[PDB]
Image: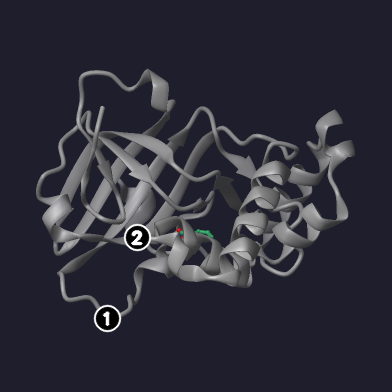
Amino acid sequence: GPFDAIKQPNRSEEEVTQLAEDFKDWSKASNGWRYSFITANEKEAVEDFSISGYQTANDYLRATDTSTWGVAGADARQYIRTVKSALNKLPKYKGTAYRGTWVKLSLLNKLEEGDVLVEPAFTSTSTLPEVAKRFSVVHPNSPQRLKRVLFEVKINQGGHTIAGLSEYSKEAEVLFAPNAHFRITQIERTSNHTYIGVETVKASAVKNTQKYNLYSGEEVEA
Ligand SMILES: O=C(O)Cc1n[nH]c(=O)c2ccccc12
């Protein structure tokens, strides 16, 4: 049953909450020597990323022209740099994670196994499909048709757990720095939903395939 971990009914609140707490505990217990260099500003930035910080950071990273942001752009650049610095001091996660989002139908209709998807913003994922699906429920106004997409992400690089610092949100969250690349390993289009299996890949390792910007739908040059 491909993607049944996503499709199937959700586990109970008790189980999902316990799994998220275990993941937070594991994250803290996995802090390494690099964590001893984390700063107060980095902790403040990561701790509030999931509730509000990601909204501004990801808009800046998706902006067509950042000179239009004025003074807020300087703040956004500082925040992005701080979160990226913090991430490299936090434990890696490898294994499977999940991401719910909305993607342009016009891009989805082009996608094949082996294509590479590039996320210009930070990429937020959860180890829990229940949490990922929560971000597939509504979208803001769009003149282009958007479709619900549930990603099953095989992570072998790039992902770091922020769950140890996210005291105020128990989402079992694994975060990627901006511009993360994901190679499609399987696609299913069924009952108006789209399920995509992807594997993390290093940008410099991507060769002789087609890259697409996941947000804009535009081709990304080799
Ligand atoms: O990028 C976003 O809009 C947030 C987000 N989207 N999708 C997810 O699956 C997810 C999981 C955990 C924490 C944030 C998220």
Please indicate whether residue 190 sits to the left or right of residue 154 in the image: left
Q: What quarter of the picture does the C terminus occupy?
A: top left
Say which of marks 2 and 1 sits in front: 2
Place of residue 193 in the rendered image (x, y in percent of width and height, measured from the top left): 20, 61
Q: Which amino acid type is marked by label 1?
A: Asn
SS class, disc 2? loop
The residue lying furthest to the bottom in this view is 141
Label 1 neighbour load within 10 Å: few <14, some 14-19, many 20+ = few
Going by the image, does 14 lie left or right of 206? right
Q: Quadrant of residue 35?
A: top right
Q: Is residue 99 visible?
A: yes
Q: Is 119 or 173 nearer to us in this picture?
A: 119
Dot 2 amino acid type: Thr
Which residue is depicted at the point 50% across and 45% down? 178
Report which residue position mark 2 lands on.
Answer: 64
Seen in the picture, residue 201 relative to 52 is either above or below; the reply is: above
The Cα atoms of the two marked residues, 2 and 1, are separated by 18 Å
Q: Which mark is residue 141?
A: 1
Q: How many tags in the picture? A: 2
Answer yes or no: do the residues labelled 2 and 1 have beta carbons within 8 Å? no
Position of the N terminus by quadrant: top left
Asked whether, in this view, residue 90 is left or right of residue 151, the answer is: right
Q: Is residue 78 above or below residue 168?
A: above
- For the residue with label 2, is its CB less than 8 Å from the closest atom of ligand 1? no
Asked if residue 3 is positioned above or below residue 88 in the image, the reply reads below
Q: Residue at x 57, y 48 (%)?
A: 175
Give how far across and how far down residue 17 sits, in percent: 65, 64
Q: Secondary structure at mark 1?
A: loop
Counting from the top left corner in percent of width and height, residue 123 is at 48, 50
Q: Is residue 211 left or right of residue 31?
A: left
Going from N to C along the chain, the mark reached first, 2 or 1, is 2
